[PDB]
Image: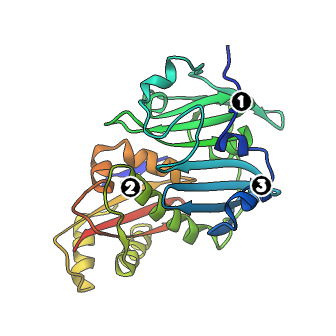
Amino acid sequence: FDVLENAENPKPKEGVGTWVGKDIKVLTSKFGQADRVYPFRDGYKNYVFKDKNSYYIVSTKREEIVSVYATGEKVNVSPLKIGQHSAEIFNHTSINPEPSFKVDGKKYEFELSDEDLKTQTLIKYGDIYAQVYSDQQSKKVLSVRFLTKEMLADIEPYQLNSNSTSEEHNKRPVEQNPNQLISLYEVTNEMRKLKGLKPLKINSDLAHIASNNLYEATSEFTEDALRGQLDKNHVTYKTTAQNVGYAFNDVPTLIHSWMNSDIHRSRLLNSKYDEMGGDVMRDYYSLIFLEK
């Protein structure tokens, strides 16, 4: 299995883009209590809000919203829209190929590749940014992440120019890895729901195999080790496959890389699979799929 590696637009007037900079209590009042709240490295906290028609990963720092990943059938990501043609964004929107900014006086300049401009477009809206995720096949908007320049420097989702330096990071809290795995499952199922596919059920035996396979691999991901571990664990199945990612900092970036790789995309959006199980530890992400 191939291991994948890591003159302006006004501010939004409505939708999730207006949440950036507000206190997290504004969403708790609107939606009620979050489904999940957990810390991650460098002093951020994630709040997950979800229902049948919407999915939000809201990041905060000192209770201020600094980022919102949004997707689903009924989310307001104005001026964008989930399901719109991605080519329609560029007709009336200022896009810079080498976006540049300062975070606490330190300059950050990104070198956006061909794939990044078409399927991970970085757009400046007022004083904030938006990452617009598009499908390489359908060319439609899948999800949008509105975020501040300091979150963007921390995530570093694009290659930095030689003049820039990557940020240093503190220890991951104990809550991070298990919550990134839950977000990996949830975002995988949100992508499947946009294409009218059934969500995959979480299988604890596949998650165990994924964790051992990942631990054994970092002490390559062969198909004989996967099919051998399934037979060794007496798991019954018709077909199986695995998606892997290295050095990723967040689930939206990881999913974008799998969605823009035909082989990984075909596994995520496979109509025949009905179960999945994975693991997240440090820089690695692994997700095993199964057709019972």
Apparent side of residue 103 relative to residue 263 in the rendered image (left or right): right
Residue 22, image x and y in percent? 79, 48
The residue positioned 63% from the left and 47% from the top of the image is 155
The residue positioned 58% from the left and 21% from the top of the image is 95
Mark 3 to mark 1 CA distance (whole Å):
19 Å
The amino acid type of the residue labelled 2 equals: Lys
Q: Which mark is residue 193?
A: 2
The amino acid type of the residue labelled 1 equals: Lys
Dot 3 falls on a residue whose secondary structure is helix
Instruction: Using the rendered view, name the quadrant where residue 83 is placed.
Output: top left
- Residue 162 seen: no
Residue 151, image x and y in percent? 70, 45
Question: Pointers 3 and 1 in contact (CB under 8 A)?
Answer: no
The amino acid type of the residue labelled 3 equals: Val
The residue positioned 41% from the left and 52% from the top of the image is 191
Mark 1 = which residue? 11
Instruction: Please state which of the two labelled residues, at mark 3 or mark 1, is closer to the viewer.
Output: 3
Residue furthest top as drawn: 7
**Which of the two discs, 3 and 2, labels the residue nearer the N terminus?**
3
**Which of the two discs, 3 and 1, labels the residue nearer the N terminus?**
1
Characterize the local packing of mark 2: few (<14), some (14-19) or many (20 or more) Cα atoms within 10 angstroms. Answer: some
Viewer-side residue, 249 vs 57: 57
Residue 92, image x and y in percent? 55, 17
Instruction: Using the rendered view, name the quadrant where residue 33 is placed.
Output: bottom right
Mark 3 = which residue? 26
